[PDB]
Each structure stands twice: as structure tokens, then as C-alpha cells.
Image (cartoon, rainbow over all chains, first blue to last red; front, top):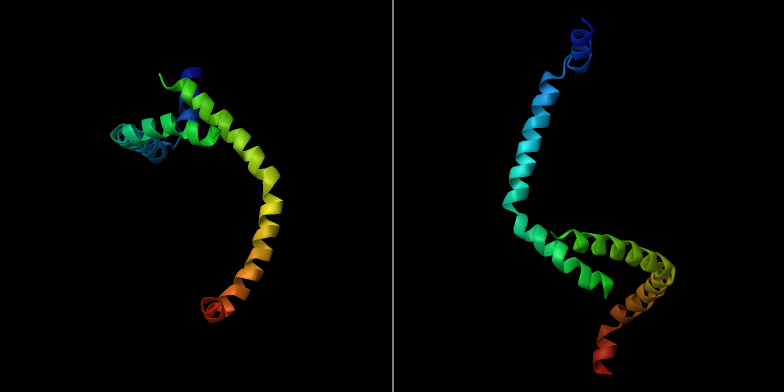
Length: 52
Length: 51
């Protein structure tokens, strides 16, 4: 009973919100992998100019 | 693997922000007065070219 009450409190009406959370997570992760070369370039080459 | 570079970037960003925030009021006052003299130069472009 306690576990069911806690699960109901945690997942009352979060259906659409959790759906949006999962969809956003997967979209952002896929797009981030798709653009990993620009991210690596930024990380590598930001330091020289900034420290200059 | 590129985490030391991330740390370097963050520390440099903080230092550069500090330097820019220290040097910004003079830069913007100079930009105001440079706007004044640039307006003056624009109003007399023909005079400058003839000169």
C-alpha cells in the first residue's frame, strides 16, 4: 500500500510530461551525436583563443 | 578524453570575463565619444575625400 501510494504521488498525471521528457531526451541525444565533430572542435580550439 | 580542455576553456572563460568587465567602462565611454566623432566624419565625407 505504501509503495502504491508513493508511486501514485510520483506518477499522478505525468503522462504527457514524461512523454515529452523522453522524446526531448532522445532527440537531443541523437542531434548531439550527429554534431559531435563541431562540439569536439569547439572544445579543442576554444582554449587557445581565450587564453590568448 | 577532452575534459582537461573543457576545464581549460571554463577557467579561461572566467578569466576573460573578468578582464573584459574590468576594461569595459573605458571601452564604452570611448565608443560614445567615437560615435560623436564618427558622426562628424560621416557628415563631412566629401570634405575628407577632397582633403
